[PDB]
Each structure stands twice: as C-alpha cells, then as structure tokens.
Image (tube, rainbow, N blue to C red):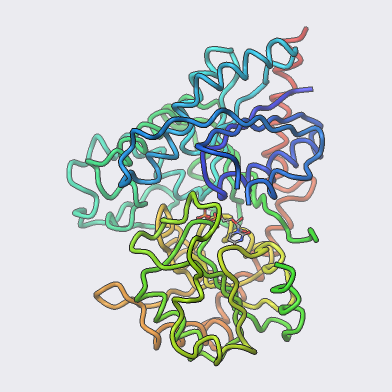
Length: 465
Ligand SMILES: O=c1ccn([C@@H]2O[C@H](COP(=O)(O)OP(=O)(O)O)[C@@H](O)[C@H]2O)c(=O)[nH]1
C-alpha cells in the first residue's frame, strides 16, 4: 500500500490537522503514514496529539536543527520555514532508510511553509504535495503572491484599493497576513520563497469545504498558468469525542448553549492593556465564559513555540475579577481540551483569534464566532468570516487598536443573547449541516481526498509493477 511521508513545519495548528488527515488516510483509504518531525527540541501538547494513533501511523523525530544563529527578533515564519529547510540533510537520511526498508514514500506531504522539503522529494522521485491548513481565500493569496510581488512595489499597507482575487473576499493591503507586512524582513522573503514553490506541487489539499468558501474554491479549481490541482478536503478536525477534566466538569454544570468559550489558539496572547479590557468586559457582560488564558506580551505570537507557561497568567487579572466571576467564569491557564469544549452542549459562542482549525472546529459544532484576529493570516480570516461568510461578529477597536471593556461586553452580549448574533448563529447552523454533507461517502470533500488517494494507489501500482 502507498506509504505517505508527512513533514510538518512547526506549530500545533499544522500538526493537529495533519494528524486528522493521516487518520483519514489510514482508516478510510488503507494507506500507511510516517510523520517526520523537524524541530529544535523534544515535542511538548505535541505528544498528546501524536499519541494513540493507529499502528499504520509511525513518527520519526529528526535531530534538532541548529537555529542558534538566528536573532531573538526573528519572526515566526522565518523560524518555521528554516526548521524545515535546515532539516533537509536529516530528511535525506530518513528517505534512505525508507528505501532500505522497501518503503519509499508514494508522496511527500508538506504544509504551507515546508516547501524546501520538495528538494528531498525530487531527489528520491517522490511526488510532492502540500496540505494547506488555512482558507481557500488565503491559498489564493499565496498562489498570487509571486505575481503581486512582481507587480506591486510599495509595502502592501500603502495600497489604496483592496486586493480582490477571483472568488475572494476583498482584503486591504494593511490586512494581508503578518509576514507580508514588511517586505524587507526575512519573514517576507521566506513567505515569498514558499509561495514561488507552490507551482512545483503535484496537488494542494486544502482544509476547507465547498459551502464554506464556494466562490474561492470554484476560482481555485479553474485551470490557470502554473496552477496545481486544488482539492478541498475539510473540515478535517478533532470532533471532540475523545475522553482539562475540571473545566469540562464545570461546563457539564452550565445551561445548554450558555457558555462563551474564549481562546487565542496555540500561540496567541494579548498586550497587558488588552488583557485587562477583555477581562473587565467579560465580567461586565454577565455571560458565562470559559477562557483559556496566557500571560500578556507585546508580541501577539510570543507563545507560538512554548511548551508551557513560565509565569502564572492569573496574576495578570484585574482586582476582584476572579472573585466576581467565580461562579459564571472558568479561567484555565495555557491549554484547554478545545475540541471537547466546542462539541459540548453547554457551549454557545466562541471568541476566537480566527486560527483556521479553531474556526473549522467551531463550524463543525455550529458555534458562532466573535472574530478577534491576532497574527499570521488571522485578519484575512476575520474579514472572510465577518464580511463574506457572515459567521462572525467583530468588536470595534479604537484608533489606538484597543478594544475597550464596553465594546467587549456589547459584542459578547450581541453574540450570546442579542439580535446581532441571530444572523451568525443561523449561518453557523447551515454550515454545521454542510460540514456533515461534505464528508459523507459521496460528499465533495470526501470525493476530493478519495481522488488524491486513488492517484497515490495508481502511482504505487505502476512503480511496483
Ligand atoms: O487551549 C487550546 C488552544 C488550542 N487548541 C487546539 O489547537 C489548534 C489551534 O490551531 P488554530 O488554527 O486555531 O490556531 P493556531 O494555534 O495555529 O494559531 C486547534 O486545533 C485547537 O483546538 C487546544 O486544543 N487547546
């Protein structure tokens, strides 16, 4: 059977969907999968995700890459991209051992920043594929970026008209994903470099689905200059049926649909001032909430690589906040069993950083959103979710960028109980239905993944014969 090697670039938001993808490949398509894990140190969260997999899935952990030459100011996308790039020598060794074992992969699947691993795929005559863990809208942006880079000579924030790619929500230059915001920085150089390599992929599998981004998917699937086949295969998520304990026990004690979940992904934190206003506004709202909290930082993605929290986040909360909210709020530091929370009947809303896994998980459970983007492509996702899909409400930030407690309370109440939240709640109901539809045996996302697996089985067949 085809053996598929999956090489994630660092990030829980890459590993998680890739694990869901691997499980589908083994359980639904009878393939074997090996994760080849590049990084700087042992896995953290990561082990919980890689644990308990079918034996048709193995993991190889490469020697840690030397990124000691990088300045502490290095942007995450540089670090993420270079972790895969500098790992190529160790990846070659792993491929040699696959060859010796009679298990040369039928495909090498990288994620959105891992395209330099294509060098190893090409060297071993293994078809390269990209598993793209965020939206068809942002994928369109990535595929266009080589052209945009060529045709536009200002920093993107200076553009006076929004970018409006076929089928895509318009996005202002100033809202393009974080690594696009400073074209002199290595983060842009690595972003650009990756995007230039997308045309080398034999296929791009994208974690989204037709009803969610119909216009962008249609556009992506139209023949184009140097454009690879694009396969929507989502929503590939943890549906939250696995057996942290205390916060779920708390949740069990709350009324149906009553709890606002609040979480900023695996790597997001707020400034001090924003943490303070959010706490105060959550309390003001008088809504029930379950907040996964991290210590504040001036850098929104400062926790991206962190295995744990050195400081106690609770020490940053305002006077009396924990007292006032003792019954109606549950504050959990650093990590929650999010898939379980979003699938829980007592959950009714999600204040999200708009990371795409969090978004998909929320869609699959019909949970409406407040869109609170922080970094990476989250602002692009927030524009898509609020202006096009219309499944998120957005808080108003002041001219200093601060969302004040009054706005927090207003939007929370709007989502949980108010008229403004009925539109988004209804839209999420429709998307929840659609999420089921597309993953049925003859659902569009299932069809797309099946086409890829079939291509891999055929390739293996031809090679071995
Ligand atoms: O406390 C948390 C925070 C995050 N997650 C999971 O981590 C992933 C976060 O990925 P996402 O794309 O939403 O954002 P990222 O972490 O990449 O910014 C999602 O699967 C979440 O369910 C979790 O289990 N517990």
